[PDB]
Amino acid sequence: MTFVALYDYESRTTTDLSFKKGERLQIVNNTEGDWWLAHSLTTGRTGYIPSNYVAP
Amino acid sequence: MTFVALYDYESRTTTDLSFKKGERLQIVNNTEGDWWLAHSLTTGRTGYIPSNYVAP
């Protein structure tokens, strides 16, 4: 259910969450799933993807 | 190792990857881990966090 921040994190974009070590966080269930850093073998581009959009 | 895009996805920020259905993608191993949408019970803010930054 609930996690705790091991480290400070400063947001790098408009969608990530800043937090300081020790905060208590709850994971939100979204349709998109976990996000992974991926490389497209098709296009050569790279960045984060919604795991629920892909399959092995 | 390798996944395939089930759906089109259009990037919403500077760090996500756009792709069209059918592309082949490889997951990149990063230090940050998976990213989760989280809600901070401490601050009330919400957004994506690097899973490796937190523990239960």
Image (cartoon, coloured by chain):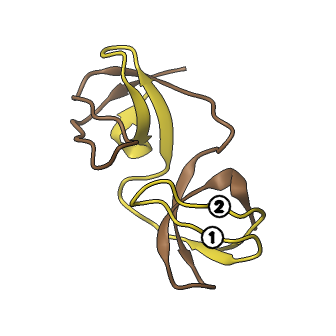
Chain colours: A brown, B yellow
Position above or below: B11 against A3: below
Mark 1 highlights which residue?
Answer: B19
Q: What is the secondary structure assignment of the residue under circle 2? A: loop
Name the residue located 22 percent from the left edge and 41 percent from the top edge: A10
Q: Nearer the viewer, residue B37 or A14?
A: A14
* B35 on left or right of B10: left
| Residue A43 picture location, percent across and down | 58, 84
| Residue B25 picture location, percent across and down | 63, 74
| Residue A48 picture location, percent across and down | 50, 60
Q: Nearer the viewer, residue B52 or A30?
A: A30
Mark 1 or mark 2, earlier in chain? 2
Position above or below: B39 against B3: above
Name the residue located 35 percent from the left edge and 35 percent from the top edge: A17
Residues marked 1 and 2, same chain: yes
Q: Amino acid at mark 2?
A: Tyr
Image quadrant of residue A1?
top right
Q: Distance of mark 1 from mark 2, alpha carbons? A: 5 Å
Name the residue located 21 percent from the left edge and 36 percent from the top edge: A8
Position above or below: A41 against A38: below
